[PDB]
Image (cartoon, rainbow, N blue to C red):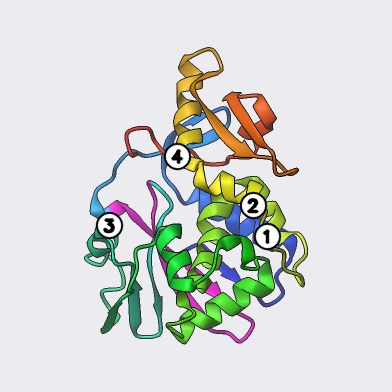
Amino acid sequence: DVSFRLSGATSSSYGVFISNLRKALPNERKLYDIPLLRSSLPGSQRYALIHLTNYADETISVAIDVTNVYIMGYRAGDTSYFFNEASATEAAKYVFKDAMRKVTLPYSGNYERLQTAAGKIRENIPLGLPALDSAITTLFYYNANSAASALMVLIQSTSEAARYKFIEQQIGKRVDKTFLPSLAIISLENSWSALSKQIQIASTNNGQFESPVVLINAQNQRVTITNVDAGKVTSDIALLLNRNNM
């Protein structure tokens, strides 16, 4: 299992962790040096388990679908926690079976539900390694009115960081500091499927998208991305969702 420990963590060690998380995802092809994820897998191969330990030596085991890098759920101690969604229910037949206590979280794992359960938007929730420390703690003790927020930190610090080098870079940059993520980071997160699809299309369409993707830049302006060189976006995105898995 890919593992991260906060104790002694550096920018590099957070980099190694994300790099290993990406390598744990099966792919048969790369397009533009970007791993193309598998379109489907049997249940016995569909899931990976990531361990994260905070500075207080408290560990959570996080289950991801390796075809799409969505978090299905997590284990802390002898309790498993799964999102209230059909994919996570299916995951529960494979992972954390040895955890005797079983909680269904009161939301699905999508940002709309989590932001509503948390009472706040991602833009106002700190990221960075101190933030990840407190999210692990929040989840380890399942403080339920604070769990949605902690899960958004966790998802962004694992799934989203693996999908985008810029997100990885920004989270790992200053290990003793946090930041509030930009509209540019949020638009990357919201647009992963669309970009993925368009980059696969681009490979067969002379470098050009069939449908443009609108992102937000570092200056908060809407930008239209229509090819694989536009905004150097192919050197940011680091995994592709398979077009047969959308």
Locate residue 187: give its quadrant: top right
Q: Position of residue 89 (x, y in %)?
A: 24, 64
The answer for how far apart the CA atoms under marks 4 and 3 are is 17 Å
Q: Position of residue 39 (x, y in %)?
A: 33, 38
Circle 4: residue type: Ser
Circle 2: residue type: Ile
Q: Position of residue 24 (x, y in %)?
A: 47, 51
Range of residues picked out in magenta: 45-67
90 lies left or right of 238:
left
SS for dot 2: helix
Q: Residue at x 55, y 63 (%)?
A: 121
Q: Which residue is mark 4?
A: 193
**Residue 171: assigned label:** 1
SS for dot 4: helix
The answer for how far apart the CA atoms under marks 2 and 4 are is 16 Å
Which badge, 4 or 1, is on the more N-terminal residue?
Answer: 1
Q: Relative to residue 63, is residue 137 depicted above or below?
A: below
Q: Which residue is mark 3?
A: 87
**Residue 167: assigned label:** 2
Locate residue 180: give its quadrant: bottom right
The answer for how far apart the CA atoms under marks 2 and 3 are is 25 Å
